[PDB]
């Protein structure tokens, strides 16, 4: 089977030992206390779980004899036993790609990677534990952006003048990746280092998204700043603007923000985070109680150059629900209800 | 994505080459002869299969610079192609955990591990081929015990005075691990070395088990002995007592036993095994024909220090069926009918 | 759980470092242009995808102290992100076996391997991109052959007199592997190297195949020739004859062929391929328009001893459909409709 059967194994010279095994060992013991309005649902969803986000990966680089740009590849496994999921992950569930790099024009990757917009949403703005609100939270229809996405081509520019970089990507959408749709998206992000500050801007457009009986277009915009000061204080702040248009003329808009404050001293880092989605507006009308927010606190100990220990507490306050354009409830990260979470964890890199 | 995204890869110093790849290569060619009472069911269930229980694992240890107890981790894949199943296993389907160890207080593991009770049920008492009766066999409702279980914290004591050790564990149940329940369980085992003998006792309690339209509590108790004699004879014997209470007032009790005899000489080991479940009692009344038993013989050849070859033959005689508390047939390991199995196998450890 | 619990890990001497990690990094960017007769279906199925056929494997050999023939084993992962599928593959989805080998009598493998017949169908006769027609295409009922198959024992002879080799195999069927049937199959292939030519012949019989409310018997025969000339010209040609007999007395026949021409000069290889399935005959009557064919062109660049780059174009013309013996449509590789495909790709072996 496959594009060339096992011919590579029969005719090519094996490049023995040209790989690296790597892994992130990551365990979070997390107790969730839900307040959904239903005592049984709270008992099911809440309680103590172990969130095992350990993963194994393989990666390598190769200088082909007949081609100047260096070939790069990566295959990274999924989380081996996350909370709320069964055990076991396949290889290739996380960033998994081939590509080429050259110091002059940067790096082009093909495969499964983070979109330029999602990368900024994810880090720094989803940490610590802000992601239920800022990453995959929100009430807007269609697809505000992809996150980790297969069938993508992504270009990461060089760091021009040691100060300015661009990431650009296009790819197939989720249904298109199964031969079940013709959705697609394109995106671009830019970063500018201004001394102790970094400026970020990003865009993503999704097209031909099928949902709630309509076809959707989404456009999402993001601006952010990150900074670190000499007294050990650092911060980030991000503003995010989401627009969606359905094929029946319905328009939706929602915006969001995320901010974080960190104090690093010695082997310790203290962190506070806040994120909110504001009320969704549909066809000029504000939908009441469609906002979300989360406040988070974290203390982290640099127990080793390769590892951290941390404790975290957060409070999620979600929207009360809304209907999509087909008169059914629209799923959001608030569907299961509000909760608080107390957790301790370890992360280790080999 | 995740509790801390890809921050570990970005900010931590990679602890290169600090891992081990290990594996058990295990293949059993097994012919089954079923006598279910339906000739077509016999043809489907029976016949020759290959039972590929090979698996790959990763593990390592790390002395963190700022923390005295040693960090340990393991990620083990599932069986790559077992009999009666499709091919392919993910990483993390078997014992997969992080933990800490210190010579004074032993070892604590968090993740997916064997329960204290199941570890004794599994070894030595399920071997060779006694498991259909003694491990997952039985007629009792609820969950008599978990076996390999995610969302567990397990403490293994040191071997005090070269004689006495304890294993204790608590964890979330199966539905709770999907956010769909609040089942939980706790267990404890103790081992006492009296020269050539070892004494074993174990307990497990499961709570809030949802099954057959009821909520269940289970309590399971186990006592056993194992012995090694230098004329080459070794043996084990176990008695197991299981009780279950449903929320509609039903009580069930069942007990079981397992015994094995071994003669080891040179590169050879002969083994006989026997296990039985006795009649289930429901509400003080014994249910007739709800018992099971199995007799097994095995010859094992130590073909290498790292590997064994073995041949095995066993006869399973199962219960004749019983209803659960929702007036439908209760699934047991006897549902598919009686069978004999003849097999040869290899196991190899790298 | 398992035939021997975790006893290997507790009692056997670990053969550390007796393993190899290997991989094929394989990425194909493929644009599909469908002409199915329905514009929506054309839009869903067609478009650009990445076909990531990268996979990771583990393999090794061990000379047992007490056994002459060398022990061999392999565990190979599946495709990490193929087109039309989700991401993630388990270990063991591809060739995964244990076995023994000796220079005198060849090699026996137990586990998941290609059948002798399928190996010739796959390479050379399905390349480049002829497989939709010649590999899993075709309209005949039952199972014309297995491809990669679990529960197999396969014997590969030595190359006698440097000229003649045999592969023979038997195994359980797909439902038998789940204990849901008693299908099985046997096959044999032979190869003869006569100067610049290689001659190939193969047979496979499948029995007790359940499909379309019937039980099927299949017999498939194959003859082929491959040639390599010193001026850089090479070719292959293969003929395939398939017969099937259903348990209600219906008989079916179909034949097929595949041919390819290659010109290799320096670091370049040009390739043209053609394959066709001819009209199916059912109970002596030809069913019109049940034939398929494909024409394909490829240019391949040997970018490295370990890697190739290639570009490829093909046009698939499929049958218009047919009913099975239960009066429902019989699925074939033409069910989704005709299409053209343009692609570029890379393959790399480490
Ligand atoms: C849980 N039963 C599994 C069965 O689902 C399958 O293994 C799946 C595997 O096929 C899935 O992968 C498959 O389905 C994915 C969506 N869930 C998309 C990718 C696809 N290859 C993995 N995500 C999980 C394994 N347990 O085959 C092995 C098994 C044990 O029988
Ligand atoms: C550049 O950095 C901007 C970060 O500031 C984010 C705060 O944005 C305020 C959004 O509130 C408007 C909601 O209607
Ligand atoms: C210290 C380990 C020695 C274990 C030896 C094996 C013991 C075999 O005992 C079997 C007893 O037979 C049980 C009959 O059923 C008992 C009914 O009472 C329990 C209620 O279910
Ligand atoms: C050996 O190589 C065989 C090549 O055969 C080419 C195709 O054979 C003709 C098939 O046509 C039969 C029509 O039913
Ligand atoms: C060394 C032998 C070289 C082989 C060349 C002979 C093969 C030529 O036969 C081609 C026959 O094709 C005729 C029609 O193909 C089948 C119908 O097409 C299906 C359209 O749906
Ligand atoms: Na719960
Ligand atoms: Na989990
Ligand atoms: Na997506
Ligand atoms: Na069978
Ligand atoms: Na199997
Ligand atoms: Na369980
Ligand atoms: Na499409
Ligand atoms: Na895919
Ligand atoms: Na098959």
Image (spheres, coloured by chain):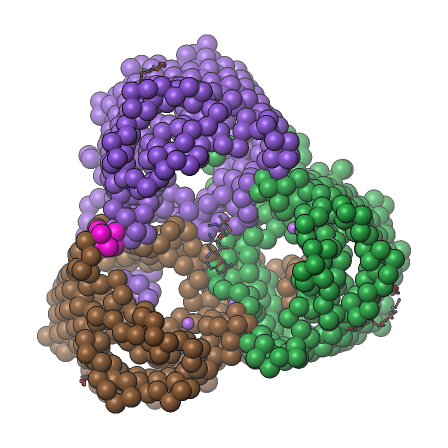
Chain colours: A brown, B purple, C green
| Res. B289 in view | yes
Residue C127, percent across and down? 72, 67
Name the quadrant containing residue C177: top right
Q: Is residue C72 left or right of residue A322?
A: right
Residue occupying the point 78% across, 67% down: C290
> Can the viewer see residue C167 in this picture?
no
The residue at the point 43 percent across, 23 percent down is B290
Q: Residue furthest top?
A: B231
Which residue is the extreme one toward the front? B327
Q: Is residue B42 above or below residue A135?
A: above
Question: At which x and y percent is residue B121?
Answer: 37, 27
Residue A44 in magenta?
yes
Residue lying at 23% horizontally and 58% vertically, measured from the top left: A308
Characterize the magenta stretch by its predominant secondary structure. helix
Number of numbered labels in the structure image: 0
Q: Quadrant of residue B158?
A: top left
Q: Foreground: C302 or B165?
A: B165
Q: Quadrant of the N terminus of chain C?
A: top left
Above or below, B142 against A267 in this view is above
Position in image of residue C104 (x %, y %): 76, 37
Write down the region rendered in magenta.
A40-45
Residue C256 point in image, percent of width and height: 81, 63
Q: Is residue B82 magenta?
A: no
In the picture, measured across the screen, residue A250 lies left or right of residue C281, that is: left
């Amino acid at each position: 089977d496959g594009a060339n059967s096992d011919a590579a194994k029969e005719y090519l010279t094996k490049d023995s030992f040209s790989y690296e095994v790597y892994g992130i060992i990551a365990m979070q013991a997390a107790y969730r206390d839900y307040d959904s309005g239903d005592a049984k649902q709270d008992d099911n969803l809440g309680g103590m779980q172990l969130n095992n986000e350990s993963r194994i990966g393989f990666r390598g680089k190769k200088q082909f004899a007949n081609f100047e740009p260096t070939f790069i590849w990566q295959i990274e496994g999924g989380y081996v036993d996350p909370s709320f999921g069964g055990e076991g992950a396949g290889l290739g569930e996380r960033d998994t790609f081939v590509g080429f790099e050259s110091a002059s024009w940067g790096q082009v990757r093909l495969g499964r990677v983070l979109t330029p917009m999602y990368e900024l949403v994810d880090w720094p703005a989803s940490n610590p534990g802000l992601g239920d609100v800022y990453d995959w939270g929100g009430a807007i229809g269609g697809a505000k952006y992809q996150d980790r996405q297969s069938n993508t081509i992504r270009w990461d520019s060089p760091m021009y003048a040691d100060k300015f970089s661009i990431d650009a990507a296009v790819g197939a959408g989720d249904k298109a990746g199964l031969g079940a749709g013709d959705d697609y998206w394109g995106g671009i992000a830019a970063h500018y280092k201004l001394g102790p500050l970094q400026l970020d801007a990003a865009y993503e457009g999704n097209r031909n998204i099928e949902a709630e009986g309509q076809t959707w277009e989404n456009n999402t915009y993001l601006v952010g700043v990150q900074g670190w000061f000499e007294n050990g204080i650092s911060f980030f702040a991000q503003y995010k603007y989401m627009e969606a248009d359905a094929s029946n003329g319905v328009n939706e808009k929602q915006d969001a923000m995320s901010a974080g404050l960190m104090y690093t001293t010695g082997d310790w880092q203290y962190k506070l985070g806040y994120a909110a989605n504001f009320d969704l507006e549909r066809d000029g009308k504000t939908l009441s109680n469609t906002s979300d927010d989360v406040v988070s606190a974290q203390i982290m100990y640099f127990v080793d150059p390769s590892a951290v220990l941390y404790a975290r507490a957060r409070m999620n306050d979600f929207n009360e629900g809304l209907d999509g354009l087909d008169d059914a409830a629209r799923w959001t990260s608030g569907t299961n209800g509000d909760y608080n979470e107390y957790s301790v964890g370890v992360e280790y890199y080999f």
